[PDB]
Image (tube, rainbow, N blue to C red):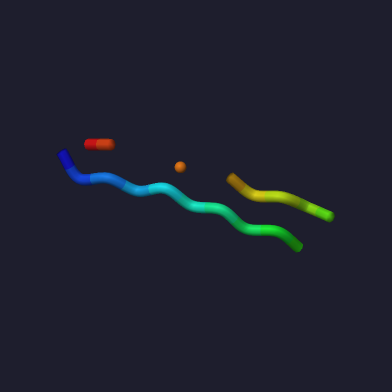
Length: 18
């Protein structure tokens, strides 16, 4: 399967398999 893992910090924190 295709995979994605995402992490972002602006605090506003943003955290994402077919």
